[PDB]
Structures are given as structure tokens and as C-alpha cells.
Image (spheres, coloured by chain):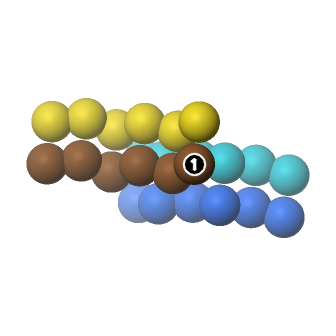
Chain colours: A yellow, B brown, C blue, D cyan
Amino acid sequence: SSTSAA
Amino acid sequence: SSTSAA
Amino acid sequence: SSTSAA
Amino acid sequence: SSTSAA
């Protein structure tokens, strides 16, 4: 699982 | 599962 | 301005 | 301005 912002 | 914003 | 996910 | 994920 992952949480990301770019 | 994932949560993401770009 | 903003872009977001929760 | 902002980009965010939680």
C-alpha cells in the first residue's frame, strides 16, 4: 500500500 | 491500496 | 489553488 | 498553492 503526492 | 495526488 | 486526496 | 495526500 502507498500514499503519495507530487 | 493507494491514496495519491499530483 | 490546491489538489488533494484523503 | 498546495498538493497533498493523507
Please report the residue visible at 24 percent of the width from the left and 47 percent of the height from the top: B2
Looking at the rendered image, the quarter that the C terminus of chain A falls into is: top right
Q: Nearer the viewer, residue B6 or C2?
A: B6
Give residue A3's position: percent from left, percent from top. Answer: 34, 38
Give residue B4's position: percent from left, percent from top. Answer: 41, 49
Residue position for label 1: B6
Q: Nearer the viewer, residue A6 or C2?
A: A6
Element carrying mark 1: loop
- Estimate how packed mark 1 is, as few (under 14), some (14 to 19) or many (20 or more) residues with alpha carbons within 10 Å: few
Please report the residue visible at 52 percent of the width from the left and 39 percent of the height from the top: A5
Q: Is residue A6 above or below residue D3?
A: above
Q: Is residue A5 above or below residue C4?
A: above
Judge left or right: residue C2 versus residue C5.
right
**Disc 1 sits on a residue from what chain?**
B
Q: Nearer the viewer, residue D5 or B5?
A: B5
Looking at the rendered image, the quarter that the N terminus of chain A falls into is: top left
Please report the residue visible at 41 percent of the width from the left and 60 percent of the height from the top: C6
Q: Amino acid at mark 1?
A: Ala
Give residue C5's position: percent from left, percent from top. Answer: 47, 60
Q: Is residue B4 above or below residue A6?
A: below
